[PDB]
Length: 178
RNA sequence: CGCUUCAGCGUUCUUCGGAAUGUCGCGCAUUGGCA
View 1 (cartoon, rainbow, N blue to C red):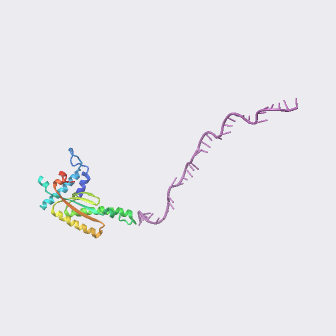
View 2: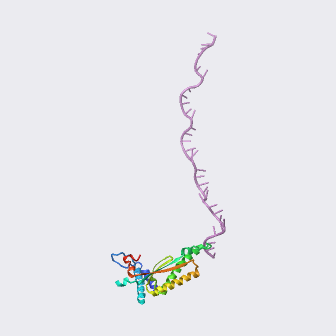
View 3: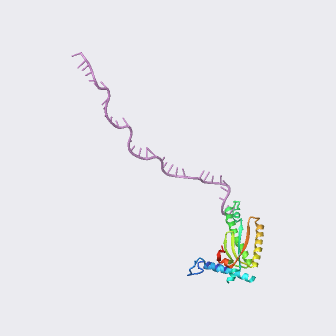
């Protein structure tokens, strides 16, 4: 599916989600498909956990992870070899962030569609509200919290927090999204 | 038999241009970088 999700992104980025419509065509078809695919998996996991009333109940979790001391780590250079270190240290933090995201999605059995957006040193993911997914976050955070301690003794850290959000919250009904 | 008046006067007193220019405006070695 990962190759398919890349395939959609390359072609459907220019395509608008809705055409010849009064509302703004500010959403791409790939974005519309990606959000639908991510939400569909989230709903399925909740149902496996076991319309208008469906929106009211809390079916999704808002989960974000942020690295700590990323800017301190980049300039940790002695300066004996600073030009190469600065480039690679930033790259390592960027790729290590992707590795953490991929590891979390693999445990939850979710595609890259669930990663709604990323910022340097940060990840923004949409996950099902199922208690099984909540258990994984406890396991995943504890695993990566110990791994960073093993490798970087307080030089780097990650924290994960999850907030339960209902279906209407995603639609931004009553301004609850922001 | 000389005597006297006059003893210099009026008028230019410097002028017109150039008023600095061109060249260099830190370099090297160590630090860095690359191997």
